[PDB]
Amino acid sequence: ARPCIPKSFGYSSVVCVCNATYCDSFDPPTFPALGTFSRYESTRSGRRMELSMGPIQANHTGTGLLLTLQPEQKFQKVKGFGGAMTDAAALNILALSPPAQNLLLKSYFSEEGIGYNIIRVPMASCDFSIRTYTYADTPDDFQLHNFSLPEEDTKLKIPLIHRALQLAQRPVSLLASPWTSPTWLKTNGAVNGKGSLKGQPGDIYHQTWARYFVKFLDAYAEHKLQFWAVTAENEPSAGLLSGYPFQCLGFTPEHQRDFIARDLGPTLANSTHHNVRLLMLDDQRLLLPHWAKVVLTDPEAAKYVHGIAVHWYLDFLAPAKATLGETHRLFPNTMLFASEACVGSKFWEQSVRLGSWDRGMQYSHSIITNLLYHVVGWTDWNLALNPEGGPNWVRNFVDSPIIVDITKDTFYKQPMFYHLGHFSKFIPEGSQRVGLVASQKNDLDAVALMHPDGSAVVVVLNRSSKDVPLTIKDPAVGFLETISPGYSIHTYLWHRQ
Ligand SMILES: *[C@@H]1O[C@H](CO)[C@@H](O[C@@H]2O[C@H](CO)[C@@H](O)[C@H](O)[C@H]2NC(C)=O)[C@H](O)[C@H]1NC(C)=O
Ligand SMILES: *[C@@H]1O[C@H](CO)[C@@H](O)[C@H](O)[C@H]1NC(C)=O
Image 1 (cartoon, rainbow, N blue to C red):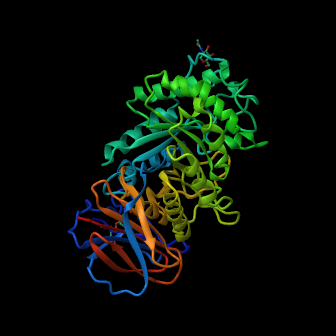
Image 2: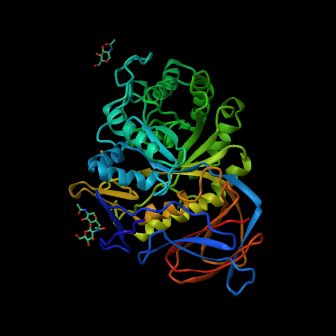
Image 3: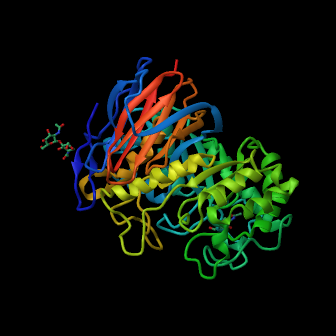
């Protein structure tokens, strides 16, 4: 329906300017005819998920790369795609005028948007908050009588989460992560820095913390929200580092292992929220496979663990094979999930680069790498940030797919937003990743998946400058002649039957 209004801010590509009355949206997706394929193209030069269509022919004209689909080779089923409703995001969204707010939300969750179906919810404060707080700051309330939701939840997060779902065509799954416990449950009695829960698993500190989760879930239920899953702790490894600057709670693997086994596991199960799934790690992939060895080879722990959460920040220091691959090998029936699918940094680039194609490309390349190694879903970090990368009470380091310029009642959609869309929009929950055999070494990044209605979706990412002539063969249907233009991402969709 509405094309992208491009703006340049001096970087490799454009953002799409959206404001109170105008934002680029899609039409309902169409189920086109057998022999016909759909193409959604985004390019550094400035095309944004542009829809074209073509023929799948029964003869093969090319001499180039041949990506051959292999519907038989079957891998993981997709849980979904989303982002985090952090204090900072909630705060930027809420700073736009209501009409603008909806264009933003529709952008992510509506079928006119990119159809997100996951939302991560931090449990109380983290670095993307304007203040350090937990849901029970009153010291030595082991019973948690004073536990309650701040205005952050009742006025910012919960209202938007409702609106997100209202707007969403898919059913959306909520995931919660805690950053810190009340500081009185902690060994160092501070929201950050090195320090864990006091005593050890089974004890009153651990039982309380376990109960916190249930209270947290209880509270969101009163506001008519269910969670699909929680993570045992966000970045547990961080709470082990001397003078770590933001909200954290250290667990070593063994510590997490026992906390899950003795406390969180049972208490959750023993609650009305027993159906909520527990995900472990929720940390850097480099800590795998070890972390999984330690938690999952203990039966009493692993009976409680539905999957392993991972982060993207530190991936350059761990390849996928050695981490996610080896972990899947060892633990095939424990799904791997990316709960903090974020980056967009360096030492020398600022937090937010308005219209950087490069970060867009990192995102999609990361999602593909993920999918090729059995990962079932993704949660980007903040749904929205300001132009400074804020607000962050410690220090703004990350980008976000949407940037809110509060003074102008307008928001900007980064290349990233479209790089996630090339997936989030066309790979609903249930989709299964299938085989896709390249005929020769090449510079592209490609993944194939099968929509629950039996039809096909292939994302092709050209991270190089050169156009790469391309042929996708589907033995049930024929051949897609195409080119993958340098610095582009393409989603190809077709019926198979
Ligand atoms: C929100 O964005 C839209 C689109 O960029 C702005 O409307 C455009 O205004 C320019 C210049 O006045 C025209 O070239 C276009 O025809 C308009 N777009 C339309 C009508 O589709 C709009 O001004 C923005 N809202 C505010 C308050 O600035
Ligand atoms: C709950 O929290 C406050 C902190 O404002 C504390 O002083 C109060 O006594 C607490 N509990 C009860 C039973 O009122």
